[PDB]
Image 1: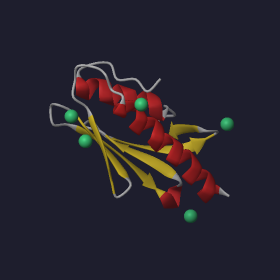
Image 2: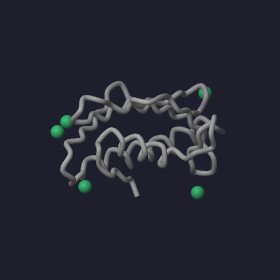
Image 3: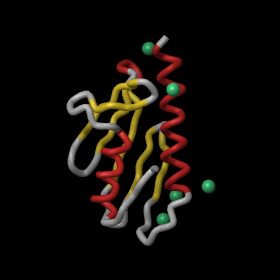
Image 4: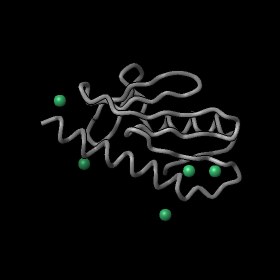
Length: 106
Ligand SMILES: [Eu+3]
Ligand SMILES: [Eu+3]
Ligand SMILES: [Eu+3]
Ligand SMILES: [Eu+3]
Ligand SMILES: [Eu+3]
């Protein structure tokens, strides 16, 4: 049921994030590491964005300089359980604010 579906969709999310930051071209230095399955993106100002799996809840969590956001699987989409906003939109907003330049995963 939900456990396999969660692993499938989260593994795809991890690869999309990693590959894009792998090919990051812009001026700002952005680094992405995977430690204990957790992704940590580090910006030149020392700020970070942290992305982890919450297995019991089948959620992906995002921790940014401004706050914490929790996402449910919704038809291949990841939706914030407090606001309805999409993961990609909230990640792009946070990364753009913390890099001081446009960061898109699209
Ligand atoms: Eu490549
Ligand atoms: Eu670097
Ligand atoms: Eu590195
Ligand atoms: Eu389970
Ligand atoms: Eu589909």
